[PDB]
Every structure is written in C-alpha cells, then in structure tokens.
Image (cartoon, coloured by chain):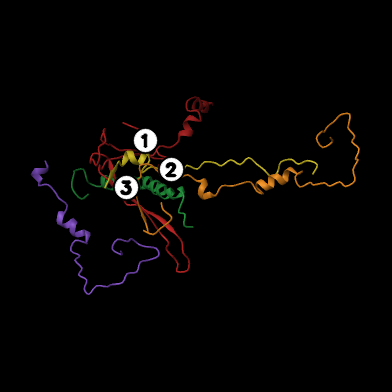
Chain colours: A green, B yellow, C red, D orange, E purple
C-alpha cells in the first residue's frame, strides 16, 4: 500500500503514554525501596551521595 | 421456502474503540509533573 | 492533604503518602518528583528485517526520565476491608461467649 | 389478482385463459435480495474500525522524503 | 541534492563533475556548538546562586 496508515498509527503514542504512567509507578516503588534501606540504616542527617 | 425468516441479513453495530492516553495519567502526572526538555 | 488514585496492580494493597508543594510550578524541586519529557519520535521506513521480507515499520521511541526529589515517604499496607464491613465485629464476638 | 392478494377468507378463483405461460422467479425470494446486498454481514476493516487518540502529546514525525504514505 | 535529501526510499544518485571538492565540516558536528556555548553546564557562583 502507498496510501499510508490510518488513525491506528496514534496507538503508538498511546502505548508510549501508557508506558509513561507505568514507568512512574515502577520508579516510585523502586524509590521507596531506597528509603527503606537508607532510613533503616544509620542515616538521620542530610548529606550528599546517600 | 415456506418460511423465509430472516437469517442472512442482520443489523450490524460497530462498537467504538477510542483507546486514549495523554502523556501521564492523573496519578503519574500529579506525582511527577511534566517538564518539557 | 490530597487524594489521587490509580488502578495499577502494583498498588493493589498499598497506600503511600508523599509530600509535595501545595502549588505546583514548572521544573520545581519541591515536587516529590519530576517527569522530564522529550517529544516522542515516530519514524517510518520500509526495513527488510530478516533479510528475506520487506515490512513498513512505524516505530515510536520514548525519550524521558523520572527523577525523584524528596527522600520522604510513608508506606501502608491496608488489607481486610471485606472482613470488617461484610462481617460482624461487635455482636458476633459476644455470641462466642455462650457457656 | 391472486398474486396481489392473500389470506382471502372466502377464497378467490381466476381462470387461466392463456396459451404460453412463463414464470420468472429470480426476484421472488427475499433471501436473494439479502445476498445481493451482502452475502455475509458487512464488517468494517479492523484498521478503520479503531479510533485511538492522544492529547497534549508532542511527537516528531520522521518519514522518508519520497514517502507517499504520509502521517 | 543528497545534502538536502533525507533517507530516500528509492535512493539518490549523483555524478561528481568537479575538478576539486573542498569540505569544511568545522560547523557540522553538533557537539561543537554545544561546547562553544557551554563546555560544561553553566553553574552560578555559589554566592551568586543564593
């Protein structure tokens, strides 16, 4: 076909946008994992690189 | 054909499929507000 | 406080409380995190992947990063709604005390 | 006219005063008309029956200069 | 011309008809412009930042 795609081509951006939301969820939970370990350990003061 | 009751012609209805997503949903956008780079 | 909900299975039994600036501003640090977005690229080329067939591949390539700012959260695992609202709590317990 | 009427309670009678009689039944069946419309219920192509969309989503479209099928 | 065309599907063919062809690419590489403006990300002096 030389006509081109129909509106279904926008599903590629939808897939990306759905992944964008899921990536925020995965990153949030992975960040909480960082807090669990760091706050469990002896870090009760602000410092760079923790 | 004594009884030509309808069998070969139906009222066809097409179910809509407006699959949509905008950048991030309310949950991800409220937590991680979008900044354009 | 404010309340925001999702339906991702990864929070099926989680409530997490995270602080954020009451009024959100572009590219702020006081937001709990940031989502740095770059326009998504969509490209169309009749690639001959596999060496023996030709297919038009229209591909979307995301380009973004999720960054956290505030090292603060409270995580709750809230379960058992049905065991409390569906069943008895007060008279059901008194019924057990029959000698 | 027997062809035009029906369910006539007292009945009706017509006398066939004719020599050469022809019967063309190509248009009598209702099923034939239904098949001529569509032998099978019409279905819209999956590519067209779908309507995905996105909002506030910035994209860069990259097609070959000589691509006819544009996005 | 090939300089202007982008990923042509059917392709492009050109004949060189020049006795000589100089090529000045000093400004072509995009990293050069980024470096010229900012060898490193611009950061305010500590006193200027507060």
> Label 2, label 1: how many angstroms apart (C-alpha)?
20 Å
Residue C4 badge: 1
In-front residue for pair C88/C11: C11
Q: Chain of mark 2?
A: B
> Label 3, label 2: how many angstroms apart (C-alpha)?
31 Å
Q: Residue at x 18, y 63 (%)?
A: E26
Q: How busy is the neighbourhood of tag 2: few (under 14 within 10 Å), some, or many (20 plus)?
A: some
Residue D54 picture location, percent across and down: 40, 43
Q: Is residue E39 visible to us here?
A: no
Q: How busy is the neighbourhood of tag 3: few (under 14 within 10 Å), some, or many (20 plus)?
A: few
The quarter of the displayed image where residue C5 is located:
top left
- Evaluate whether label 2 is on the same chain as label 1: no
- Image: D8 above or below D30: above
In the image as oriented, which residue stretches furthest toward the bottom? E19
Q: Residue at x 19, y 66 (%)?
A: E24
Quadrant showing the C terminus of chain E: top left
SS for dot 2: loop
Residue C65 picture location, percent across and down: 30, 49
Q: Chain of mark 1?
A: C
| Residue that carries the numbered disc 2 in the rendered image | B20
Foreground mark, 3 or 2, reads 2
- Evaluate whether label 3 is on the same chain as label 2: no
Quadrant showing the N terminus of chain E: bottom left
In-front residue for pair A10/E9: E9
| Residue that carries the numbered disc 3 in the rendered image | A33
Circle 3/circle 2 CB separation < 8 Å: no
- Image: B2 above or below C83: below
């Amino acid at each position: 076909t030389d006509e081109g795609p129909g509106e279904v081509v926008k599903a590629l951006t939808v897939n990306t946008n759905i992944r964008n939301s899921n990536n925020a969820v995965k990153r949030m939970l992975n960040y909480l994992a960082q807090l669990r370990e760091v706050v469990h350990n002896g870090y009760n003061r602000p410092k760079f690189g923790i | 054909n004594y009884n030509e009751k309808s069998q070969r012609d139906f009222r066809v209805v097409t179910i809509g499929y407006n699959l949509a997503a905008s950048r991030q949903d309310e949950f991800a956008e409220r937590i991680y507000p979008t900044t354009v780079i | 406080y404010d309340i925001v909900s999702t339906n991702n299975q990864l929070f099926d039994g989680k409530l997490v409380v995270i602080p954020t600036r009451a009024v959100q501003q572009e590219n702020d640090i006081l937001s709990w995190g940031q989502f740095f977005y770059v326009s998504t690229v969509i490209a169309d080329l009749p690639i001959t992947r596999g060496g023996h067939q030709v297919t038009r591949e229209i591909a979307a390539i995301p380009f973004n990063l999720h960054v956290n700012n505030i090292p603060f959260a409270l995580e709750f695992k809230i379960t058992g709604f049905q065991k409390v609202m569906g069943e008895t709590q007060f008279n059901g317990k008194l019924a057990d005390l029959k000698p | 006219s027997i062809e035009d009427q029906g369910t006539t309670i007292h009945g009706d009678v017509e006398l066939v005063v004719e020599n050469e009689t022809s019967a063309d039944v190509s248009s009598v069946l209702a099923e034939v008309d239904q098949i001529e419309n569509n032998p099978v219920e019409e279905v819209l192509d999956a590519d067209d029956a779908v309507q995905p969309t996105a909002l506030d989503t910035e994209v860069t479209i990259v097609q070959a200069e000589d691509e006819l099928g544009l996005i």
